[PDB]
Amino acid sequence: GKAAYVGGADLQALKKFVSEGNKRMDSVNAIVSNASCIVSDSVSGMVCENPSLIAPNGGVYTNRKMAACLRDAEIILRYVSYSLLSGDSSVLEDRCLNGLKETYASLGVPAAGNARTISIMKATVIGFITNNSQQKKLSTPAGDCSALASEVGGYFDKVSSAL
Amino acid sequence: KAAYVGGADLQALKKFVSEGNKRMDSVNAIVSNASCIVSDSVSGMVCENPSLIAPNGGVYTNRKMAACLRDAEIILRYVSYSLLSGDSSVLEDRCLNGLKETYASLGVPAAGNARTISIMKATVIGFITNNSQQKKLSTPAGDCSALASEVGGYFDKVSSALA
Amino acid sequence: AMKKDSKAPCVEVFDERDGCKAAGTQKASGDDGFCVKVSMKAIGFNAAEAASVTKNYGIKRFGA
Amino acid sequence: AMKKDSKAPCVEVFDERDGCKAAGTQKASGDDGFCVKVSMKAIGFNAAEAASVTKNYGIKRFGA
Ligand SMILES: *CCC1=C(C)C(=O)N/C1=C\c1[nH]c(/C=C2\N=C(C[C@H]3NC(=O)C([C@H](*)C)=C3C)C(C)=C2CCC(=O)O)c(CCC(=O)O)c1C
Ligand SMILES: *CCC1=C(C)C(=O)N/C1=C\c1[nH]c(/C=C2\N=C(C[C@H]3NC(=O)C([C@H](*)C)=C3C)C(C)=C2CCC(=O)O)c(CCC(=O)O)c1C
Ligand SMILES: *[C@@H](C)[C@H]1/C(=C/C2=NC(=C\c3[nH]c(C[C@H]4NC(=O)C(C=C)=C4C)c(C)c3CCC(=O)O)/C(CCC(=O)O)=C2C)NC(=O)[C@@H]1C
Ligand SMILES: *[C@@H](C)[C@H]1/C(=C/C2=NC(=C\c3[nH]c(C[C@H]4NC(=O)C(C=C)=C4C)c(C)c3CCC(=O)O)/C(CCC(=O)O)=C2C)NC(=O)[C@@H]1C
Ligand SMILES: *[C@@H](C)[C@H]1/C(=C/C2=NC(=C\c3[nH]c(C[C@H]4NC(=O)C(C=C)=C4C)c(C)c3CCC(=O)O)/C(CCC(=O)O)=C2C)NC(=O)[C@@H]1C
Ligand SMILES: *[C@@H](C)[C@H]1/C(=C/C2=NC(=C\c3[nH]c(C[C@H]4NC(=O)C(C=C)=C4C)c(C)c3CCC(=O)O)/C(CCC(=O)O)=C2C)NC(=O)[C@@H]1C
Ligand SMILES: *[C@H](C)[C@H]1/C(=C/C2=NC(=C\c3[nH]c(C[C@H]4NC(=O)C(C=C)=C4C)c(C)c3CCC(=O)O)/C(CCC(=O)O)=C2C)NC(=O)[C@@H]1C
Ligand SMILES: *[C@H](C)[C@H]1/C(=C/C2=NC(=C\c3[nH]c(C[C@H]4NC(=O)C(C=C)=C4C)c(C)c3CCC(=O)O)/C(CCC(=O)O)=C2C)NC(=O)[C@@H]1C
């Protein structure tokens, strides 16, 4: 119920405990430093492939419903960013996904829309981690982050499957 | 602390400045896009003169670059307040008075400042006149030529004070 | 005079004519859905954005 | 369980190996310039970003 600050020997142990610690911190940093554009580009992509989502009484018609959806995409992205930091999905599973499928069935949050937002978020995050992003590149030493792109891909897939 | 102007308070304000409704959209366009305006203008400064980020150049190292980005936002925000109120007295007194002399002390290069300001000016005017290419304003369509000339004049005030 | 404290007027413009209201935000008298907020805030340093511009300044974005 | 509280883990990653330090931010001990901060925060609604997506979803950006 407070902020955790991890540095010094605490962080050195965390970074030995996870695989590829230094590249992993860069990967986390890429997600959280670009969180707003990742979310907006993915939800925008949802809509432009299916613009009836923003037609009257569609899923994200009106600013309140669109705002709730952008908020949810960010929540999900941040649980994924924490899974990549820690390298396990326990917290994503128990505190974000657990019961979420049933919530969205009652509220009328359509599944095909969510799955596209998630796939675009996954594609966008992988593009950053692999420096295939075109408007912005990461400021890191050059190298191969393919293993970490795969792993974060699995966290997103867990979300997709859960929904 | 914060002042809030609405209802009858705000209705009379939109009456003492010209084109109240388009004016408020114009202010909202500046502040809602403050980060991209600032970052595209400082970036263009550097891509036009990349020696600004070479060793001991004006925005070499993150601290100097961060300070410059900060100043560009400060200046952009004093201009947004000028467009809101229809005059430049606060910009002149609280932002420009003493600033050229502070910059010549710290060696902040005038050539670079002049270019940051010109791109921020071109960017704001582009938004207000529907010449922005990635994102448009969510407004009724029409002509905002007069308000583009006015905000241009406030930017021109900054350029002359720092030239 | 410019005070060297980084503080600038932060303007917020609100258009809530769709009627959606947030608990704890009726800071002024009115029901037509319009409001303008102004506060003076110290503008902060953003190292992340600084790093990004240093790396990425040479990329043309937004169809500029 | 998902609590419907809108709270998510907000991770911030710091690399301050250039030596630059902001007053008041030294919350942990170390000698290498690295820090990770984690907190749970409620993710808020952003009407301005909602407005922008509603208007601009059909424009391809970023070389995407
Ligand atoms: C706020 C970001 C933005 C969105 C979103 C959008 O739709 N347009 C946006 C910004 C914008 N920029 C300009 C104009 C210029 N931008 C630059 C800097 C970039 N040019 C480079 O060569 C470069 C380094 C490689 C940059 C980075 C420049 C130089 C301009 C022109 C300034 C001038 O003197 O005319 C605009 C204005 C309209 C346009 O597309 O030019 C906008 C809206
Ligand atoms: C965070 C913004 C960003 C920057 C900055 C950058 O450099 N790259 C960025 C984002 C990014 N997006 C993608 C991939 C996709 N984006 C979309 C949505 C847009 N496509 C549309 O058709 C549409 C409406 C007209 C959009 C808005 C889509 C569909 C994708 C591909 C996803 C998929 O097909 O599964 C990436 C990935 C790399 C790339 O360039 O595609 C990135 C980095
Ligand atoms: C419904 C959920 C909407 C939405 C509403 C929000 N408004 C937020 C802040 C806010 N709104 C106003 C304007 C309002 N207050 C007034 O006094 C009057 C006119 C007399 C009106 C038109 C103000 C002044 C404020 C700031 C309150 C303050 O000074 O602290 C708000 C908070 C945003 C956040 O916490 O991130 C919300 C959520 N937002 C949405 O997405 C839907 C469409
Ligand atoms: C995919 C992730 C990227 C890519 C990442 C690489 N980073 C490499 C080395 C590296 N990164 C850091 C900073 C990181 N460590 C931390 O503790 C934190 C903050 C808490 C940060 C943000 C460091 C210190 C290092 C090693 C030392 C250095 O060179 O300064 C790296 C080299 C291989 C490796 O170290 O395993 C890579 C490949 N590189 C890419 O090309 C994509 C886009
Ligand atoms: C250049 C500025 C733009 C352009 C702007 C236009 N806005 C027009 C009418 C209008 N705008 C608002 C919202 C505005 N008024 C407020 O009080 C506040 C918040 C405090 C804001 C955000 C309203 C309520 C209106 C009234 C008309 C309506 O609801 O449709 C407008 C029509 C001409 C005029 O009213 O003077 C224009 C042209 N339009 C463009 O194409 C560029 C990009
Ligand atoms: C010098 C002006 C730099 C710059 C520094 C800033 N850091 C800011 C926040 C911050 N930094 C850390 C990491 C630091 N604290 C530690 O305990 C250790 C390791 C043991 C390190 C590496 C943290 C944890 C934080 C957040 C503090 C908190 O959450 O209470 C910061 C933000 C201040 C603001 O918002 O204005 C700054 C400016 N930033 C720059 O641009 C230059 C390059
Ligand atoms: C960016 C386009 C420039 C660039 C800007 C730099 N400014 C630096 C320090 C600085 N800036 C101000 C003025 C600022 N503070 C205010 O209170 C207001 C208005 C109310 C403004 C616009 C001051 C007072 C200072 C020094 C004190 C401080 O930072 O709080 C700066 C660092 C200079 C240094 O470390 O000596 C830079 C790099 N530099 C460039 O090359 C481009 C053209
Ligand atoms: C965006 C890609 C979707 C879309 C999203 C919507 N979600 C809406 C309400 C809502 N979302 C949640 C789950 C959210 N809250 C949490 O605490 C967590 C995890 C910790 C998450 C993932 C809840 C509990 C709720 C209802 C309560 C609330 O909004 O705070 C929503 C509004 C639904 C309504 O008005 O009944 C939307 C529009 N909608 C779409 O069409 C796309 C596909």
Image (cartoon, coloured by chain):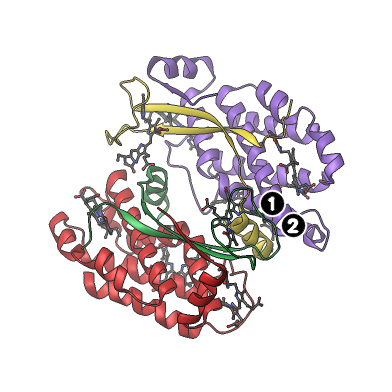
Chain colours: A purple, B red, C green, D yellow
Return the residue nearer the eye: B117 or A131.
Answer: B117
User: What chain letter is assigned to the residue under label 1?
Assistant: A
- Both marks 1 and 2 on one chain: yes
**Residue C4 in view:** yes
Horizontal side of C15 relative to C42 (left or right) equals: right
* Secondary structure state at the residue bearing disc 1: helix
Depicted C17 relative to depicted C47: above or below:
below
User: The residue under label 1 is which amino acid type?
Assistant: Val
Tell me which residue sits at (82%, 57%) in the image.
A58
Horizontal side of A107 relative to B149 (left or right) equals: right
**Residue B129 in view:** no
Horizontal side of B56 relative to B76 (left or right) equals: left
Q: Quadrant of residue B105?
A: bottom left
**Rendered-image quarter of ligand 8:** top right
User: The residue under label 2 is which amino acid type?
Assistant: Val
Depicted A117 relative to depicted B159: above or below:
above
Mark 2 residue CB less than 8 A from any atom of ligand 2: yes
Marks 2 and 1: in contact by CB < 8 Å?
yes
Tell me which residue sits at (55%, 72%) in the image.
B8
Mark 1 residue CB less than 8 A from any atom of ligand 8: yes
- Give the residue at mark 2: A47
* Mark 2 burial class by Cα count in 10 Å: few <14, some 14-19, many 20+: many
Depicted A19 relative to depicted B6: above or below:
above
The x, y position of residue A74, in whole percent, is 63, 42
Tell me which residue sits at (20%, 49%) in the image.
B56
The x, y position of residue B113, in whole percent, is 27, 65
On residue A43, the disc is 1
* Mark 1 burial class by Cα count in 10 Å: few <14, some 14-19, many 20+: many
Return the residue nearer the eye: B39 or B142.
Answer: B142
User: What chain letter is assigned to the residue under label 2?
Assistant: A
